[PDB]
């Protein structure tokens, strides 16, 4: 039952500071513009120890599957090749991506009826709020 409150289909309802977060990460202009316009759904499922997180939008469809604590290589929507590790820390999914000596952290948590995504690169945070679809 690990992650039960995360499982389901979620739709983006608000975003703050996402352009600035993408600039900090190194995302180029055209990708920032099209990615920032996207209204993704996030589809989270669990089968045994394997968690799958899909993102679907008009920009990109992505999918990761992973086991908590077990590093994996990920191609991000902006085409970075990163090494990722996702853990559960006090009920928060904490996703760390490493590439080219840089690091960013994406936290996903349940708050009331929302799934809140916080993306942090150095001092820049973006907050993205999802509701059940
Ligand atoms: O920032 C996240 O990915 C990093 C990223 C951000 C922008 C680009 Cl172009 C590529 C990758 C992320 N992950 C999620 O699961 N939901 C979100 O809303 C979300 F923004």
Image: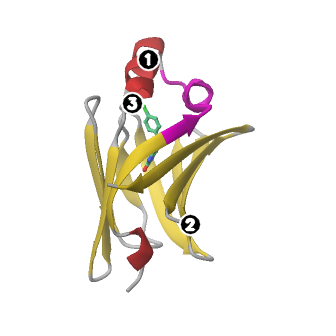
Asked if residue 100 shows in the view, the reply is no
Judging by the rendered image, the residue that carries numbered circle 3 is 78
Looking at the rendered image, the disc whose residue lies closer to the viewer, 2 or 1, is 2
Residue 20 location, quadrant: top right
Q: What residue is disc 1 on?
A: 33
Q: Residue at x 43, y 54 (%)?
A: 131
Q: Give the Cα distance between marks 3 and 2.
A: 30 Å
Residue name at image x 41 percent, y 69 percent: 6
| The disc label shown at residue 112, or none | 2
Q: Quadrant of ligand 1?
A: top left
Q: Earlier in the sequence, mark 2 or mark 1?
A: 1
Q: Is residue 109 above or below residue 41?
A: below
Q: Is residue 49 above or below residue 82?
A: below
Residue 13 pos. (x, y %) = 46, 43
Q: SS for tag 3? A: loop
Left or right, residue 18 beside residue 133:
right
View extreme (right): residue: 123
* Depth order, front residue of 43/75: 43
Query: In percent of the image, x 48 and y 61: which residue is there?
Result: 85
User: Magenta part of the protein: which range?
Assistant: 14-27
Q: CA distance from mark 3 to mark 1?
A: 12 Å
Q: Secondary structure at mark 1?
A: helix
Q: Nearer the viewer, mark 3 or mark 2?
A: 2
15 falls in the magenta region? yes
In the image, residue 47 lies at what x, y percent? 24, 78
Residue 31 shows in this picture: yes
Q: Which numbered circle lies on residue 50? A: none
10 Å neighbourhood of mark 1: few (<14), some, or many (≥20)?
A: few
């Amino acid at each position: 039952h690990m992650c039960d409150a995360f499982v389901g289909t979620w739709k983006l309802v608000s975003s703050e500071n996402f352009d600035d977060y993408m600039k900090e990460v190194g995302v180029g202009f055209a990708t920032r513009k099209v990615a920032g316009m996207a209204k993704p759904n996030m589809i989270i499922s669990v089968n045994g120890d394997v968690i799958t997180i899909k993102s679907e939008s008009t920009f990109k469809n992505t999918e990761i599957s992973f086991i908590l604590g077990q590093e994996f290589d990920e191609v991000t929507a902006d085409d970075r090749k990163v090494k990722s590790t996702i853990t559960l820390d006090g009920g928060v999914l904490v996703h760390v991506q490493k590439w080219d000596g840089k690091s960013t952290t994406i936290k996903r948590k349940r708050e009331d009826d929302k799934l809140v995504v916080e993306c942090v690169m150095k001092g820049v945070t973006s907050t993205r709020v999802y509701e059940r679809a």
